[PDB]
Image: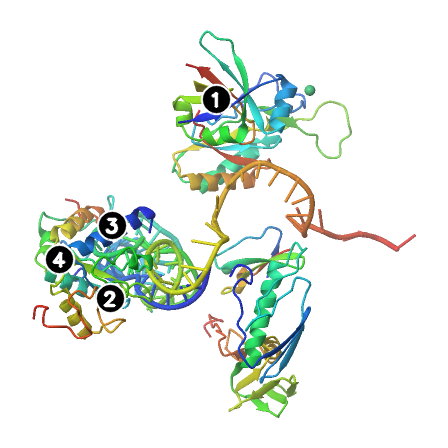
Amino acid sequence: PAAVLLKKAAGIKSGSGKPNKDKVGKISRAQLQEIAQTKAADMTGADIEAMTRSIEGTARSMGLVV
Amino acid sequence: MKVRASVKKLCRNCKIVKRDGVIRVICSAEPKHKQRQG
Amino acid sequence: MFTINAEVRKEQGKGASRRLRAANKFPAIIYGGKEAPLAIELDHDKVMNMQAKAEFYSEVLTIVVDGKEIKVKAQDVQRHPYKPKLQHIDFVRA
Amino acid sequence: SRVAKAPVVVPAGVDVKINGQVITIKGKNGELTRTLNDAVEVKHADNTLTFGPRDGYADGWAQAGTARALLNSMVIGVTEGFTKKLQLVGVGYRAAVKGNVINLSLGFSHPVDHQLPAGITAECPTQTEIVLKGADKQVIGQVAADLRAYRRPEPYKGKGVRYADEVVRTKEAKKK
Amino acid sequence: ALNLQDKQAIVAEVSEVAKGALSAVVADSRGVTVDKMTELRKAGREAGVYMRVVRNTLLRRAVEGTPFECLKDAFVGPTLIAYSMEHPGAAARLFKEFAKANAKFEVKAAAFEGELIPASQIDRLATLPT
Amino acid sequence: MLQPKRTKFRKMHKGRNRGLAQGTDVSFGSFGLKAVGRGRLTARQIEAARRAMTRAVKRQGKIWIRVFPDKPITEKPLAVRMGKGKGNVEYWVALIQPGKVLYEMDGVPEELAREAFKLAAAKLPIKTTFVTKTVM
RNA sequence: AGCCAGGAUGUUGGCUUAGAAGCAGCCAUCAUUUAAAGAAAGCGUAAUAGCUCACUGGUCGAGUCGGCCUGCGCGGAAGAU
Ligand SMILES: [Mg+2]
Ligand SMILES: [Zn+2]
């Protein structure tokens, strides 16, 4: 769902700081898009992109800048 | 109980009452917060 | 939007102004244009409530005295030295 | 409510004699009497009573509320009575019901016997769980406090007389 | 909520029934997010892409709000009766969705009934898609 | 600490503290701690209040001090008689009139400024109050 | 106002840290879901946890809410024939 498949961001669960800190993870254009698009089990609704954009934008705020 | 001049609320759970000639602060959970206006 | 009522000052001076302030109404002067200045007096609390908005100073207001509703501005305000009060608001015509 | 605005309803079988500021209630569960303050005028002209204070006082609404609450509690305790209970958490804490006298041997070299009011009954199925019943919840609470005053629940171990709904705490003494 | 949203609540209550408000009741325990997502998913996939299981319990909404159908809509107003309203149709499978959800640990208040559109008794009729 | 680098004269008369204050308007910031009473503020008290408000609010915001002692207050040592001259200068204080604005602050939340100025008042001897920016 | 119920996930995230996890202490408080989640306010847990609180809804039936101007009072207020 959003835990065991969200720990798969760049190779590690999460190892980055928000503004500019000890970051170990990055993000591509579809790496975290697929983990929310390919899954029709955890979706509250049908808008997959609605929760995909949130993860893509919070990758930067966690340390996985685009 | 802590007796002092100026009394207040340490945590929100503390209630202030006014008895015969004094003002007291009583906390239901933590006895340490018990205070009096001496 | 701002509409205030006024009265004409029967007596003017330090003693009259301080008596008015004790009576909870403060004086004011209206001048400008080519007409003689007029000494009015206003309720203090109404003006204090109205002056809170920035629009009171940045927009035209109207003052009504003896049935005449004249539109004026607010250029200078003298605040109380150490209290949330204003004394002798200044109104400029036109 | 705001001030004794919510009326009390008195069930049938509870005889009430109201005389000015003095009221008497007689039911199956004992008899009670109360003479009130000067902020009263409660009236009884229907199936129940609804309170009122006397005119000409800066106070009076709060007193009417207090009188209404007290009379409601007394009506409830005279029509059905109230009951409380105490639990003795600890080895050697023996409680015995000798009729109208309780015996409380709680780690004392000198055993202590306590008297009871004439309107209070008590019974203990064991030596640690005591249950008492009465008509007046004020007297019930007073006697319960008298019983519990012999020993308080110590936070460091958790022994001593306490109410059934009392919540004791055990934070830490020294880790040993 | 605020009066500006209370206005919209009544506007929706008197626009919901016009296009068909198939309604039901959801438990407070079944409305928990840990176990509400299943019902949300089921109802949404069955009906459309939008869902509304939000409860809007009111007494005056049973005299001037929800009731716009034939005669009976004021029996789901008081006594903790949750509101679950669905737009698409007055005879769709939304009743059957809650009937199925009943079998999976849902026995809360009123046997998932509301708006009495197809003269629905405690037992569902054959009108619903099977 | 706050003290003039040099002065024309080192000893000044006691003087008085009659009259109101000129700096009664908030100009260098958005919030101000305005003294509502009367008395004198020492450079030591000003430093204490500045440290208190610095602890209260972090690099988060700019703070201006609208006052400066400029008044040398002297005292005589212990076990000495009267006359024979004037004592050596001991410290520096200012004369504070009602309505005087002491500390101004900008770039901070309103509640944080309120708390910081309350803490500063707790250190200051003279009764003070909180004044917001004037629309005028 | 009481009462009832709800109040997830990455996340026990990554530096120091047998340990740091929402609480020696913190560097960092980000995001979707819903009416509701704040790297979580509290206690304490070595530390997790746990509940309430922030917030939301429902039962109960007309006053309540937190800011200013002030008046009179309250405690600070303990000495020796
Ligand atoms: Mg004079
Ligand atoms: Zn407390």
Instruction: Mark 3 vs mark 4: tell me if same chain.
Output: yes
Q: Which residue is mark 2?
A: E26
Q: Mark 4 and ligand 2: say if the CB distance to the nearest ligand atom is below 8 Å.
A: no
How far apart in space, not on screen, are marks 3 and 4 (Cα)?
17 Å
Tag 1 subunit: C
Q: Of marks 4 and 2, which one's residue comes earlier in the chain?
A: 2
Q: Residue at x 51, y 9 (%)?
A: C36
Q: Which residue is mark 3?
A: E11
Q: Which residue is mark 1?
A: C64
Examine the rendered structure and indicate whether residue G52 appears above or below residue F130. Answer: below
The crowding category of the residue bearing disc 3, from other C-alpha atoms within 10 Å (few below 14, some 14 to 19, many at least 20), is: few
Amino acid residing under circle 3: Val
Amino acid residing under circle 4: Pro
| Mark 4 element type | loop
Residue G55, image quadrant: bottom left
Instruction: Mark 3 vs mark 1: tell me if same chain.
Output: no
Tag 4 subunit: E
Amino acid residing under circle 1: Val
Q: Which residue is mark 4?
A: E88
Residue C19 place in picture, x, y as percent: 64, 24
Q: Mark 2 vs mark 3: give the one in front.
A: 3
Q: Mark 2 and ligand 2: say if the CB distance to the nearest ligand atom is below 8 Å.
A: no
Examine the rendered structure and indicate whether residue A45 appears above or below residue C67. Answer: below
* Residue D81 appears in view: no
| Mark 2 element type | loop
Residue F79, image quadrant: top right
